[PDB]
Amino acid sequence: ETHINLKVSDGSSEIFFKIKKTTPLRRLMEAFAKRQGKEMDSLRFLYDGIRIQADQTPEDLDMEDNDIIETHREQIGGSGKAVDYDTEVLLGDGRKRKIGEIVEEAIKKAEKEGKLGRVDDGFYAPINLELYALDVRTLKVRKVKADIAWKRTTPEKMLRIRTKRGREIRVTPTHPFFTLEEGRIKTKKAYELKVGEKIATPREEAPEAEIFWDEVVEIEEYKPNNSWVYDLQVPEHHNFIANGIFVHN
Image (cartoon, rainbow, N blue to C red; front, side, top):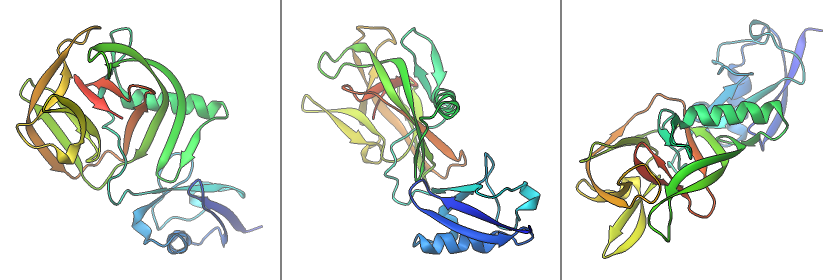
């Protein structure tokens, strides 16, 4: 047998193509893209781990049949609350760990088991992580638990925010923070923040610590290159301490 039929899937959408092993896959993915209603480079085609490039064939990537090419949507419109891989999450035991390591670990543990979740723009995985977060009614630092780890495609632009105190985080343009208007603590999306506006941080990264309202001094829009962004979902309080800042889900 020479010709090979792969299943191309965005998690939801699955289309079966059969092509011969010498064919470049340029038009397989161009066809799938048009079937999805978008042009080819708003999508990401992945075999096992590494991302394909258009001018490759089945044999040079060691293909089999019923093999799958997973596609991930490039976010147009931001809309995907998440943060940079290196964002240091503050664990419930006091230590700090980059959220990307946390999420990738959770993802391969979910994959070795049978509960890795897939969405068109990435993956999620069950987790049970004790974090430090802001108590939305006590307004002091508390312990919480995250149940879902999230790994999504990088948006077309991201925002790096740095505060007068010297805290700095790289987040998607929609990622919300805590603000204070008239005595209201509200949440504001990142792109809504203005230079000089104060966002909530922990005064110390210790339990029962109160809020330090930190003046935002730098807001930088930039084209990223990191390929994946990450987040943690924490029920009830919907936030956690990352890079010394209260980041809201």
